[PDB]
Image (tube, grey):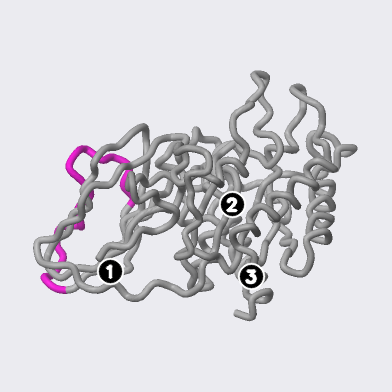
Amino acid sequence: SVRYLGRVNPATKELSWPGTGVSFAFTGTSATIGIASVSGTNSVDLVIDGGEPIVISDFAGTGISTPAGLRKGKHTVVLRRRSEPAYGSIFLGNITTDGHFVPTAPAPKRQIDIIGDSITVGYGLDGTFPCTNTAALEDNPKTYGVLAANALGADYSVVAWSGKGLIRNFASGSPDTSPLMPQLYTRYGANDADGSYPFPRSWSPDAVVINLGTNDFGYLGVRDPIDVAAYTDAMVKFVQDIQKHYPRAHFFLLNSPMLSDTWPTAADAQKTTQTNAIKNAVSRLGAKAHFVDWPTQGSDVGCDYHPNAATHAAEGEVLAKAIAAALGW
C-alpha cells in the first residue's frame, strides 16, 4: 500500500507542494510510478533502498521507474518533489511492480508543517551563484525545514511558494496582488480552490514552522517600507488561524537569512526590525510560540542570493534542536 507524503489532494493525486510524493516497498526487480500528466517543469528525488537521491527533471512519458540493476528481492522507494507549483506540477497515475507490494515501515508519529516562501521551497539551492533558478535547481529535500524534520524522525508537510509574503508579496511595479501565504495555506493542492484543504485529523502537526517576511520587507524603489505593526498583527493572526485546526501545536517563527541591517540602507535596519516584530508576536502568542534565529547568511549563495546547501544545513540543525527542546524530543 502506497502512502502519500505531504499535502496531496487524493481527488487529483497532484504533487503540487514542494516535498510531496510517495513512499512504498515492493519485492521484485522493478517498480514504476505512473504519471497521469505533467505540466510545466518539475524535478524530483527518487530514493531507492535509502540510497543517494536520483535527481529526475525530465518525465518523457510513461512514468518513473526504479533503476536498472536491482537484485530480485525487497526494495523501498521514496519519491519527493524538489520543486514548487509556480514552475509546474506532476499528476500521479498508478504504481506498479513486476513482483508485489510489501508493507511499508510504519509512518512516523511525529509531524511537522513548514510554511514559507522561496527559502522554504528551496529556491536556487543547488545553484552556483550567479545562476537562473529552474525547477531542476530547486531542492526542497535539502532545505532547513526538511533537514530539521529528518533529524527529528518526523513526517512533514511543506506549504511554500516563491515570492509570497504574510501581508504582501514580492515587491514588483505591477502590484503583485495575488494570494498571500495564509490564503494559500487553506488550499489542498496549490492551485485548488480556497478552503479546499479539509484539515483531516490524520494529520496533526506537533510543530508548525513559519518563515515569512523576506518578501514583505522588500520595498526599495517600488513601495513604502513595511507596516511593522500590521506585519506583527498578521503573524499573530496567522498562528491563531492555524491553531483553530492544530490547537496543541508549538509554533516556530523564524527571521530571514536574506534580510540584513545594511541593505537597502542602515537606517532601515531590516533584520533587527523583523526580528523584534517576530519576538513581539511570540510574546503575544504565549508559551507555545517560539522565536528561532537565522543569522544573515554569508557571501556564498545559490541563485538570486538564496541560501545554499551549507546555509540550509546549518539552520536545519538549529531548528531541529529548538523544536526538540520545545517538545521534549
**x, y percent for residue 195:** 52, 43
Task: Using residue 34 as the reference point, say whether residue 231 is left or right of it.
Answer: right
- Going by the numbered disc 3, the residue's amino acid type is Ile
Q: Position of residue 30 (x, y in %)?
A: 14, 61
290 w.r.t. 18: above or below: below
Q: Outermost residue toward the bottom? A: 328
Based on the picture, tell me whether residue 62 belongs to the magenta stretch: yes
Q: Is disc 2 in contact with disc 3, using a CB cutoff of under 8 Å?
A: no
Q: Residues within 10 Å of mark 3 (few under 14, many from 20)?
A: many
Query: Is most of the magenta stretch helix, strand or loop?
Result: loop
- Quote the CA–CA distance across marks 2 and 1: 29 Å
Which callout, 3 or 1, points at the residue further toward the start of the chain?
1
Kind of residue at disc 1: Asp
List the residue tagged with mark 1: 49
What kind of element bears circle 3?
Answer: helix
Earlier residue among tags 2 and 1: 1
